[PDB]
Each structure stands twice: as C-alpha cells, then as structure tokens.
Image (spheres, rainbow, N blue to C red):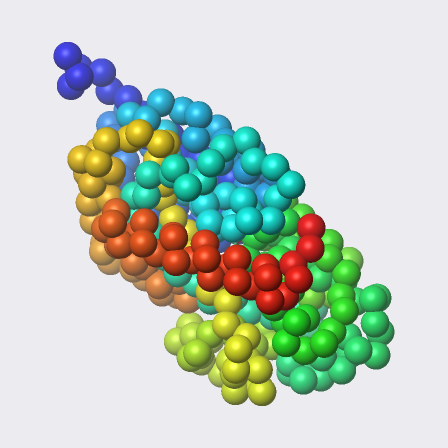
Length: 299
Ligand SMILES: O=C(O)c1ccc(C(=O)O)cc1
C-alpha cells in the first residue's frame, strides 16, 4: 500500500544555515512535523548560487517527499544570468511562497556615513575600492546592489559569498563595506548595534524597523527590491500533491508562534496557493530579468 510507508519530508535549503533562507523554513517545519511522522529534515546544501541544492531537488522523485525551500536565485533569477544551467527552473512545480521580505542596505557601524546619500558620496570618493558582499551570483542581494549602482552612478566591487551568513560575518569583521541583505537577517544585528541599516528598498517602511527610511524617502524612488522564500517541487509532481503540501504549509504559517517569529523579523507570511505562486514566480522572473538588463548585472 501507499499508507504503510512512512516517508520523511526532505526540504533542501540551498544556502548556509542561519540566514533567512534557512531560518524561515525551519520555523515552519516545527509545525509540519505532526503531519510527517517519519520526520521533517532540512538539509543545507550550498554552492553555485543555490543551484547545487536546487539541482538535487530537481532530480529527486516527483512524489512530494523532496522539496526545495529557496529564495529567488535558483527559481526565478540565475537562469537569466548564468553561463549554463543543469536544470530548467521553468519546470519547477510551485507549492507556495512562505514569505516576502524587503532588501536593505547594511553597513558596519564604523563606516562614517549616516544615511544613503552619505554612502553614495563615500562610494564616489573611493571609486572601485568599496566592496559589496552578496549571497552569491544571481541572488537578490547581487541584483539589488547592481540596481543601486545603476540608479546612483556608483562603482563598487562585487564579493560574492555562499549566502547571507558568511557575508554578515565579513561585514561585521569589516572585510566588506556594504551588503544589500534582506531585512530579516540583518534586523537582529541592526537592533543590537552590530550593523547599521541605512535604507529599506520598498515603497513603505518596515513595521519591524519603523525608524529606518525607505530609499524613496531618501531620493531614490526606483530603488525597490523585495525578496521572497518559496517552496517548489520537482517537475511532474502531481497537482493534488502540490495542493496538499501547500495546504500544510499555509496552515503552519497561520499558527501564532510562526506568525510571531516572522513578524518580529519583518518577514510577511504569505501561504499563496499553487496557481498564485506560479504566476508570482513568472512575474518575478521577468521583473528581475528587467533589472539584469537595466543595471548591466555582471557575474
Ligand atoms: O537571493 C536572496 O534574496 C537570498 C539569498 C540567500 C539567503 C540566505 O543565505 O539566507 C537569503 C536570501
């Protein structure tokens, strides 16, 4: 029979532990363990911008027991930018979006600038010398830095990492000068005074950090850059399986503790149905491609 095999749910996060990509699915997984009695196991599988872990899910059996929980790179973005691809992201089977989260500009608290305009001047004063970390080539932090440079006429050197976690280590350590992270992973550091967020790349401020202005409020209205964390299944996963999984994830997102934890970090829980999720990924893929084009995004 089917029912007599307990099967674990395996969720690959294709980025190092401790960033938002890792934290949000782990928070949610605590509320799914009851429905997957053989266990919910998150594995962090790093490399190639998120494409190593992504490929591993892509090639797994399309039974819904192996899923990718990822930010946009290996779902919507990197196939527009990379020299090659070992899988076809257009064939992901969308399950849901766990959260959307705005990106920010974050610096070390010793950087002698108080706001975005002063940061621009610092970059122009030290042209080609100021370095920006990223979460990897083709991640939203990469493209967000690029959009910033496009809109401001600045020239900064890209230093890609494997994800948020090692980038934040180096920004704290002073080994990079700026990072366009999402708010959720940078907020604890900002609150602690360990890092300093200069602006939020959205049309409104975050309720989690209400005193930090948007980029629009600082003279850069087109500096909008919002990431997200989706769940996708291998190509060919049945529609009713995807639907059942989306209902399980959506149910987790509404649980009070998951709501508290997402809210305190400025992550907006979504839980969108598979169709809406697929429409969103399509629209996002094109939106980020339009950034690649307008901002001359370079590997
Ligand atoms: O592309 C992104 O927005 C993104 C990439 C990596 C991580 C992480 O390492 O947690 C989070 C977000």
